Image 1 (cartoon, chains in turn orange, green):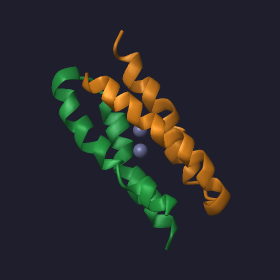
Image 2 (cartoon, helix red, strand yellow):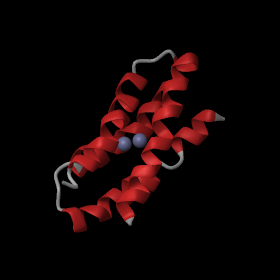
Image 3 (tube, each protein chain N blue to C red):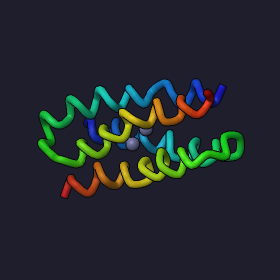
Amino acid sequence: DYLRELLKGELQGIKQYREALEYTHNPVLAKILEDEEKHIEWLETILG
Amino acid sequence: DYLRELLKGELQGIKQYREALEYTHNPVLAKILEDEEKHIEWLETILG
Ligand SMILES: [Zn+2]
Ligand SMILES: [Zn+2]
């Protein structure tokens, strides 16, 4: 069950990071959420 | 307050990923958890 508990939680971060560039205007979010966008599918691609 | 909400729970992934490789045995967690280890200090560094 742990994989689904993992996968549900990274999705909770992708949508919040896309808001934060309005207040930070930084290139850091163009690395952080750029990784979180791949990460969910990166865990999943392994399963089969 | 959004920054506190962003920061606190990336470690609710980092420690979980470190255990999950004992079941998965895959190099992808050495890209997922490799990046979550940066992600917290990445968004924390900007406020200085
Ligand atoms: Zn991630
Ligand atoms: Zn993260």
